[PDB]
Amino acid sequence: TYSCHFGPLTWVCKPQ
Amino acid sequence: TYSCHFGPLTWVCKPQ
Amino acid sequence: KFESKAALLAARGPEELLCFTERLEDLVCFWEEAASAGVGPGNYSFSYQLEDEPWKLCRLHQAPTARGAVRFWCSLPTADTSSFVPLELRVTAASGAPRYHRVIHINEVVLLDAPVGLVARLADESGHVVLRWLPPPETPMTSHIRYEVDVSAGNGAGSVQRVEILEGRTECVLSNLRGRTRYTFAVRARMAEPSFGGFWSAWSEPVSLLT
Amino acid sequence: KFESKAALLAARGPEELLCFTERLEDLVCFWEEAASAGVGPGNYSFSYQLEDEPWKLCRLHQAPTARGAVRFWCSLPTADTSSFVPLELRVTAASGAPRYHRVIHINEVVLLDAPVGLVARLADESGHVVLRWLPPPETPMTSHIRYEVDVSAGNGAGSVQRVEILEGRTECVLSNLRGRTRYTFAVRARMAEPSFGGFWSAWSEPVSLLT
Image (tube, rainbow over all chains, first blue to last red; front, side, top):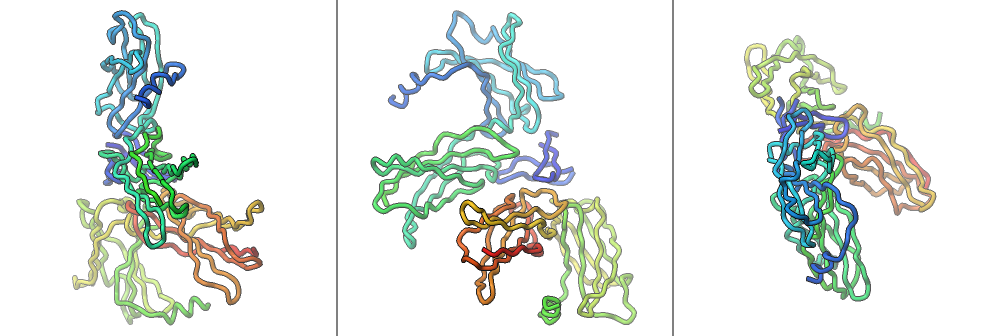
């Protein structure tokens, strides 16, 4: 559903 | 990077 | 009808386009106005657009407000209910005149169903209150939900005492308080920061202990 | 010294393949054994298989252990440190003679660096001690990290007192300690459940305070 990566706090997601 | 979708507890990812 | 009649009378102020999500795959937006002659949905157009997607127009509906005003609404089809992106909303009158303009994040306007299964217990060996419960039914991302416990009752004392609760937690031991006191409890659910945002749910059905 | 020599006289279990991740784009695996006349890293082959990627090889290094045993290690290439897939591991003698075989998940094997900037202060207003620190330097996903606080006291006075701090918190206020005592505090971090798993870090350099 979303595209995520490890950010400095938590997940930075975005809709695929 | 990872493909996550909401889950019961928290996200569910798998590497892209 | 006491609680019911209180609302008819509890007047709010200005109109506003109000949006909210219950699970994270739906979006409902509405507004309410004075009932007026043959002014139905056909006189309005509700246009939305997910950032970088073709502009879209959803179906307006109408139903009455328990107060005699009218309510117009749209339900976005799940497929467009994606989070983490800027959703632009536009409500326009068929004369060309603009009614509302808003930009939102669906992930910041959550309004969960309230918690179920509230059970209270006397932690017999210590002598106190052990508070447990269930999250909004059929709702995801369980380990994001923050809670709020509302302790109260005990004649004349207007204790409506509240204690926050960290996410994913569904148990609280009201360890230290009274002896022979009637106590009634209830609790609210809220999506936690900073990913999500939203509004405080309705109180969960109360539970009464009697120390 | 003392901790080193104490370390040097400690016990020991058998051979065991050991892997761990520090930041979340790296993996180190190693195993120890006895020195050998004519044995080098080129005596075994270290290969891995990141699910549905083909078998690959990692080159071994060899380093002496303070105790007089030798250490074989290798650190995986960045494009291979993916987090939610099974990692096939196998170490074999340079004659195809079998040595090790494990299967892991880089997310379930986190071993973070130690916390930094730990400071202790006396909350003038209430008489309370407030501890502060920062997360392991350059570590991503910091609101998922849990911390444990160690309180070790003066002269003959020391009972073992530890403190659980919830993930995301990088402060803590210790209330209820004896007066004119010397308190030395220290922190250590861990990736919280149920996403990540692993080992508790090393302690941080500590601060000491005269109540």
